[PDB]
View 1: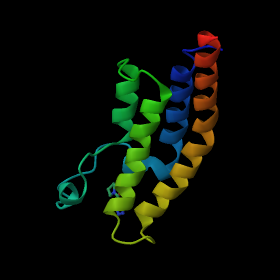
View 2 (view 1 turned 60 degrees about the vertical axis):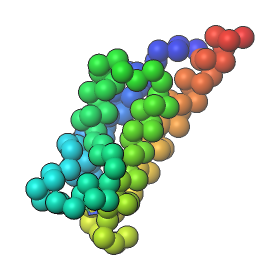
View 3 (view 1 turned 180 degrees about the horizontal axis):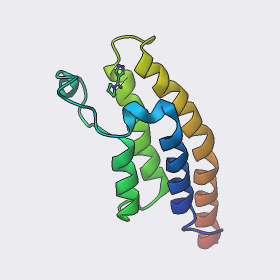
Length: 119
Ligand SMILES: O=C(c1cn[nH]c1)N1CCCC1
């Protein structure tokens, strides 16, 4: 019932993501010189270094806020891809499945800790 445990769990999950080869296109903001039309399609850029920095700054209040920003990395890739068979989009789908499989227990444990506190 540790209300704060999600933070270290998210740091460790980000470490696993940074080791995945599939995260390489998403570690840093998209290079707007290589993709000059990026901001014509994407309203809010997001990347894993920004997520990690926001977490380490103490600027997430819950793992649900972190999960919203990670999910934005994946929805941006889906919106930007010129094809559902593109290399970088395919990497995003695998990485999203890995993220979702690992974040589920983090969210469940956090919500359980809040409920126990309210009890
Ligand atoms: O999400 C994409 C992308 C998706 N399909 N093709 C490119 N990018 C983020 C990193 C740079 C490109």
